[PDB]
Image (cartoon, rainbow, N blue to C red; front, top):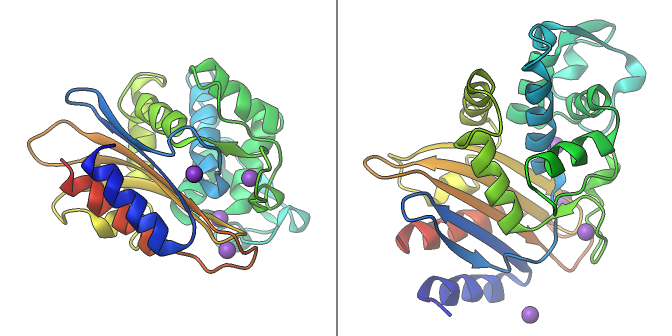
Length: 262
Ligand SMILES: [K+]
Ligand SMILES: [K+]
Ligand SMILES: [K+]
Ligand SMILES: [K+]
């Protein structure tokens, strides 16, 4: 095993949990993986798949993103920072997409799932862009249960890194759509203590975090260093105790180990 993998294994051992990392260097298309083929609960990182599915729809329904959407009291779930600001009012699918991606709003995610026809509509878009691994089974908030061994609402680090590459740097989306997604990921408010904290401060980053039971702490990022091809980095982490605390530091340290392995 590589030098990087030795250091990621040691980080994992010090943490008491289970760590998953996938890097894709778009220079030589080489990959670094740690438990790259194990399943991890996605938690809110699945918001990227749902927002991207809606973007794919907007390519033919050219006014879809401005479509208003009723926010009703019964739509509110466990974590609704933006949507609770509009109960008995409306929000557009663009506003819901940005609330989901940039504030991790769970009512926003549920509206995107509805627009897609249920969780199966998210999974279907994954299958349509070549991702045979991702699976979304539940809505918010039950998709966060993160039960050990449960395959519901999981993916693997390798699959999510490949997919995130296609949506953000590839052409799985149309060009207007891809840049909307990139802008959204760059304006995330929830990621300062996760991957971003382990990286050179000059690098540009867009990311989506996730957190859930079993101290599940996740981040998926696309990374633009200065002077070299961009990278995609996925870091998943989950823990043995159902009530375990968040460990965003593990993700920052994973990113540091990866960046220093370049
Ligand atoms: K093992
Ligand atoms: K969330
Ligand atoms: K699980
Ligand atoms: K938690």
